[PDB]
Amino acid sequence: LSPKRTRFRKQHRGRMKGISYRGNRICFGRYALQALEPAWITSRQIEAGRRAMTRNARRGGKIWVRIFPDKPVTVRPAETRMGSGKGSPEYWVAVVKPGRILYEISGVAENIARRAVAIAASKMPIRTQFIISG
Amino acid sequence: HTRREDRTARHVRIRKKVEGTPERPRLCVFRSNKHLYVQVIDDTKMHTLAAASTMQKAISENIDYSAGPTVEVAQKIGEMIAKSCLEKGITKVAFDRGGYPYHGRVKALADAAREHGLVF
Amino acid sequence: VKVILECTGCVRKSVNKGSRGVSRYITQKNRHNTPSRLELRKFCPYCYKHT
Amino acid sequence: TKNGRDSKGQRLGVKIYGDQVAKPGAIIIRQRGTKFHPGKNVGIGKDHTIFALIDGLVKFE
Amino acid sequence: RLKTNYIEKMVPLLKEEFSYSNILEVPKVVKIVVNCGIGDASQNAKGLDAAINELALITGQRPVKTKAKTSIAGFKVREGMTLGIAVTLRGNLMYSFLDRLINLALPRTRDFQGVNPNSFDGHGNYSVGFREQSVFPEIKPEIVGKARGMDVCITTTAKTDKEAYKLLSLMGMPF
Amino acid sequence: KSDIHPEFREDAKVYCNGELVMTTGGTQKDYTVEVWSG
RNA sequence: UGGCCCUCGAGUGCAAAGGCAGAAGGGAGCUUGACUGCAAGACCCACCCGUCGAGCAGGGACGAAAGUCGGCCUUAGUGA
RNA sequence: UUCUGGUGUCCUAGGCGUAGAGGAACCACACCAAUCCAUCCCGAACUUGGUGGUUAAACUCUACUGCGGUGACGAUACUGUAGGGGAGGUCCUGCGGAAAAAUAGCUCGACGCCAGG
């Protein structure tokens, strides 16, 4: 859900620039949930979706949170935006660009995988679709 | 290291050329168990101006039961390289021990070269 | 403690060419006294510039 | 509260690029440590600066 | 004088044994070194003098008071505080005092497993050392009243695990 | 310095010689060495 | 305390970056150049400041000699 | 005129591993003693003086692609300009430049210089 070591406390923002290579073909699993829309994904989404496909699969097959957040986003109180002292202890975020794999799931029959990864796509802020291990 | 007396002598020379920095007319030695070689060489054109060795004196005199280097054969090799550039027009010459500590017989090669008017 | 301290030559106030005290301040004395042969005094060479 | 903001602003470029005209004494490089070593006709300085000795051209190699 | 026969009698047996092409490869006892690890030689100055006197008299030449590689906190160990005393002895005195080990350290120990070959013969090339039995009959033994480490290490030109052990067996060191 | 002159007085004659024909000086005098283990 | 891989991962008084393993790393020998009079030209450049400097004279250190040495691996340690 | 080590300079950098070949000369070790010297302990190094036995080690020479180094074209990313799409995050065409990565590959360097047998 978060990294153990705080290398640098705060870390300023970045920006998305669409994938062209490292399309993250498939490595584990057999069914992935390929992102299409660049955006951030917090660690709490990740929690949500994971719960979704774990309790939905619920019989077999292994989940794979293919990406780990590793960058902090800060938030400031309501004090007229003076100096950004402390907000990194707030949520973490994984920058996810297009063409990227978010989950992977094996050991599950076809359509059960479709319901797991479809629901999981409902819990998550960007339009995805599920891919088979070609 | 494993070529203790090769890494050692060789690199020690590279030391003598890193900081000691002899560049213009430089005479270098090389003392092996059978012989002494010596060169007067120029860096600009990278050719040995005037060499000499224990393969020109031993044409007349040497001894083998000794170490090919002995204070006296060195005396004669500095003798010869001296009386070679004593006539060639090389007054000052940047001496460099070839990594051999200056004590000993390379002394005798130096003083031998000095007595015969090499501005040293 | 790094107190400053100045050095001085061998005075010999004379009627010669401008001869004169030659101080040279230096630092660091946290020890017993240190003289040094800083040189090029009024007279050319020098030795044992004390204090 | 900020704690931060104490930058120096110092400047240290290459002064005479390869194939410019070097005066004598002119500075070739002002550097922090020795990126470029002295070759020949240049002199290192106290702080590793690299300055030309004779007029001509600078060749980085 | 262990050297001579060692040179003419027990060289041909290894030369024939390994089936060389050159005696020039046969191993020899290259060098040894004896050292005396000390708890605090700093605070026992006459213990530094105990290193000098004893370890000098025992072996051929003087010792070497050894300086701290790097410090260790808690203990009075600055980089240089002498904790360790060695004598890098070599040449042929080597032969005389591995001789007086064969002769006054094989006989006068009390426990005897001897020398475990696979013990203390482990290397890319031999470093065979022994711990304890520092005291000898020649030195007046009843002056020390404390324990004190020691090393007796060795080298070799051959890099097997036994030919220097066998070299100790061809000499007065079996078990 | 600490010279030792390791040549003159050497004591080391074992019970079963031949194996110990030799003997060497030093700063030790008793010419007898114990058989020990074997 | 002895033997094998090694990328300069060790250190360099103190922070970091750049540097440095013929070392700027460590240890020895002698020594005070952490001298006087200076200085072409550069770099920076609102000014005030600041930085480097081939080379010369005197008088020295070290070094057999070549040569190096007018402070400290460089940038903070300071104020008209 | 090859060979032998003597020094060096452009550099793809040059090596480690397996293999071999080298003693008439050269090179280097084993050997030997000690004034100069030297080992903070030791002739280990360094030194001077001797014997002058092997090529074993080291060096040199010829192969190797098992490693190491190197490294493409093409394509694509990206980007200059001229424009456009999208509520935005950001995306796309026209003319110009153009890779890193990987893979194929490419090397076990090229020249001088002096004393030689």
Image (cartoon, coloured by chain):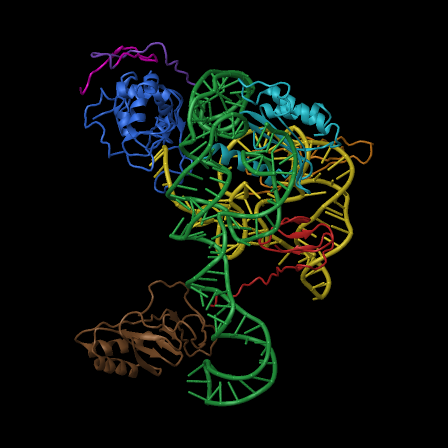
Chain colours: A brown, B cyan, C orange, D red, E blue, F purple, G yellow, H green
Magenta-colored stretch includes residue A3: no
Relative to E143, B28 lies left or right: right
Report the residue at 57% width, 36% height from top: B13
Of the pair D35 and H61, the residue shown nearer to us:
H61
Identified at 45% across, 76% down, the residue is A17
Quadrant of the drawing holding the N terminus of chain A = bottom left
State the residue at coordinates (30%, 82%): A121
Residue D39 seen from this side:
yes
In the rendering, at what x and y percent does residue A99 appear?
Answer: 38, 77
Q: Give the range drawn in magenta.
A: F20-38
Q: Is residue C44 above or below residue D15?
A: above
Name the foreground residue: E97 vs A36: A36
Number of numbered discs: 0
Q: In this view, does H39 lie above or below G73?
A: above
As displayed, is residue E173 above or below residue D24?
Answer: above
Q: Position of residue A87 (x, y in %)?
A: 40, 72
**Residue F32 in magenta?**
yes
| Residue F30 placement, left or right of B116 | left
Magenta stretch, main secondary structure, is: loop
Q: What x and y, as percent, mark residue E58?
A: 33, 20
For the view shown, which residue lies furthest in the left direction?
A59
Instruction: Work out which quarter of the rendered image holds the C terminus of chain A and state it.
Output: bottom left
Rendered location of residue E7, percent (x, y) = 34, 20
- Residue E150 or F35: which is nearer the viewer? F35
Q: In which quarter of the image is residue E174?
A: top left
Comparing G6 with E42, the one in front is: G6
Q: Quadrant of residue E1?
A: top left
Q: Can residue C45 be seen in this view?
A: no
